[PDB]
Amino acid sequence: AACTVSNWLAGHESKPLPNLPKSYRWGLVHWWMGIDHFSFVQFFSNWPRSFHSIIEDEVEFNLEHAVVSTSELRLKDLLGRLFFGSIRLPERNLQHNIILGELLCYLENRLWQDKGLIANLKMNALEATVMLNCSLDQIASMVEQRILKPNDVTDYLFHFGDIFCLWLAEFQSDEFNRSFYV
RNA sequence: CUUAGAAAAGUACAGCGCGGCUGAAAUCAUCAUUAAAGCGGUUCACUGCCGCACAGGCAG
C-alpha cells in the first residue's frame, strides 16, 4: 500500500487517510521521515491507539532512563523531541495539524497525573515563547504584571502546567483554538 | 661631548662628685523617645519485624 500515498498526496480519495490540504500532507510526511516506506499507511490506521502508544513508549523510555532526577526534570529531557519538533509546522492550525492536536489532547488529559510530574516540569523562557507565539518583550511585560510567576532572559523559571494554562487562557487564536481539536 | 681629562685624611682618649616640692579645698539645681509591620516546606523520611526497654538492632 506504499503506492497509495501517491494518490493521497494528490489530494483525493484515500479513505484510510485524513485528506488534509496538500501543504499539510507534505508537512506531515516531512515529520514522518525523521520518525518513505510502507510503515506510513498503517500508522494512521488505528491512528489514536498507535499515536498514543508511541507517545507511551517515548515517555516511558525518557522517564525510566532519566538521568537528572525523578523531579525537577526539564521538558527536553522528557518530552522535548516530540513536542518542540511537531510544534513548528506550517500555519500551526490545531485541526489541520492532527499530530499537534492529538499531542495537546494527550498532554492535557494526562496533566496532574501521579504527582503532577508533567504539570511541574521546569521550562525556560525561550521555549515558552516558542509554544506561545509571543515576543520576548511581551513575556517580560507579563512577568512584570505577575501573570507569569517564577519559582532572566534565559532561565528555567516557569512550569509546563502554568504555561499551558496561560496559553489556554490568553493565547487562543482563530485557528490555534482548543475547540478545533477536542 | 659635562669649570673636560686625575686623586685613600688617618692614627690615641674616664665627665665626675651632693641633694625633701610643700601647705587648702562642696561642682550645684530641672528633664516623656514616641508612632507601624506574615520571612515562606503544596509531595518529599512511609509501613511492617525483633527486643521488657523513652535501649539497640532487622527488612520492603
Image (cartoon, grey):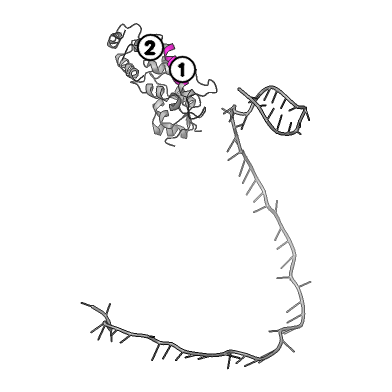
Give percent across and percent down for residue B45.
63, 28
The disc at residue A43 is: 2
The disc at residue A56 is: 1
Tag 1, which secondary structure? helix
Query: Which residue type does callout 1 highlight?
Result: Glu
Give percent across and percent down for residue B44.
59, 28
Image quadrant in which the N terminus of chain A is located: top left
Residue A51 visible? The answer is yes
Q: Is residue A171 magenta?
A: no
Give percent across and percent down for residue A134.
39, 28
- Looking at marks 1 and 2 on the same chain, the residue that comes earlier in the sequence is marked by 2
Q: Nearer the viewer, residue B51 or A25?
A: B51
- Please identify the quarter of the rendering in which residue A128 is found: top left
Q: Residue at x 35, y 12 (%)?
A: A39
The disc at residue A119 is: none
Q: Chain of mark 2?
A: A
- Please identify the quarter of the rendering in which residue A29 is found: top left
Q: Chain of mark 1?
A: A
Residue B59, relative to residue A146: is it above or below? Answer: above
Give percent across and percent down for residue A85.
37, 23
Residue A12 placement, left or right of A167: left
- Span highlighted in magenta in the image: A49-60
Residue A182 visible? The answer is no
Crowding at mark 1 (Cα within 10 Å: few <14, some 14-19, many 20+): few
**Main SS class of the magenta portion in the image:** helix
Q: Tell me how many marks there are.
A: 2
